Amino acid sequence: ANGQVSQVIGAVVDVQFEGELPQILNALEVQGTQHRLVLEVAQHLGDSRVRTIAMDSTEGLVRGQPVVDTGLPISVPVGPGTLGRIMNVIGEPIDQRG
Amino acid sequence: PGDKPPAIEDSIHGKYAGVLFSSASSNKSLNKVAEDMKYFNQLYKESEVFKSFLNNVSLKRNQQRDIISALGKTNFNPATNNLLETLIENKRLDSLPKIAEKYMDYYRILNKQESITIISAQELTAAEKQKVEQGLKKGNANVQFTVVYQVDPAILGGLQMYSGNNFLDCSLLSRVNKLKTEIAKISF
Amino acid sequence: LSTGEASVVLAEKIKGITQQNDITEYGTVISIGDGIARVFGLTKVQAGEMVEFKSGIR
Image (tube, rainbow over all chains, first blue to last red; front, side):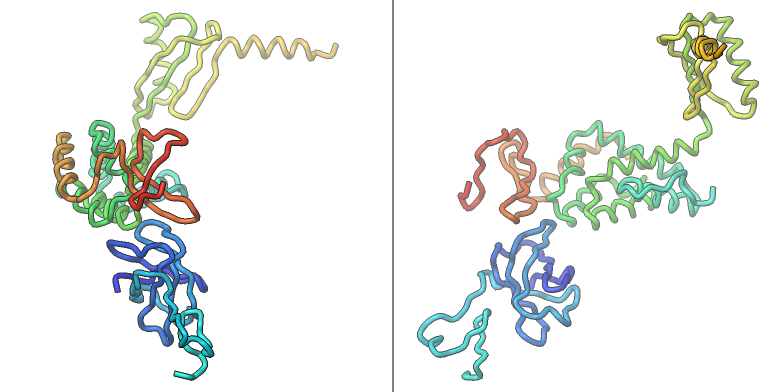
């Protein structure tokens, strides 16, 4: 959790990181949200700041909120288990089938 | 003087220079900060490594603070130290030299001494120059000034004075053109 | 204060930061985005010169 919410502009959210930055296209996860909020890195604005796009509603966020760097882009579960199963953009099941 | 800088500007360097002048002039001191900012100007042009440091933008805030402390923690007015700390936080370190210079401008505006430049075609004789001083002195008679000379005009036997920001034309060339124009528009 | 502080700043510079490689041949990326990278301290580069990044991309 080496990231912090510097600013929040609608769906776009900028995360202030320290030291190493998340590679572009990586998937960041916000901590403390009601539901899992994943942020996809789009570009590095500079000054240890990065601009990301929110995969879920950014309502209820707070500046300085800790953010964790997954280190890799959005990872979705693949395989025969997804067959016949409704999957979300972030790989979560929304069919209430476990 | 009312903790009000000479002019108010929205420019980056202008904003910091104005706030520093007001904040500095507020408590007690203006010359102390003037000497501090002047030191940076001299060092900015004399030391090459120092120039690259300020211009450097990819440097981290914590790194910039350590280098600034190494320069000097004493002999700088607290207003100057607080200014630097603010620039590092706002990544405005690159604008340091402009702020320094801009600050001195306001201070030079408060300075009462002014330089008056006289422009004349014909060479000014030692005796003639003496008479010029009495004329300029009697004109103001309430402020000291330093006189400077520069003789490379196009007019002939004309006098043109530049006093900081004011210009008064006593040149004969102006008189010649004025008459030649009015004599043409007689509409006889 | 003194004018000879350049050596003091230079000393703190070489040790304070594990950076400042051969600027005349190397540079640092200030920002990356929209297919554009803001390299830093890449002096002496020629217009149209071919540069290479860390990962090998040119």
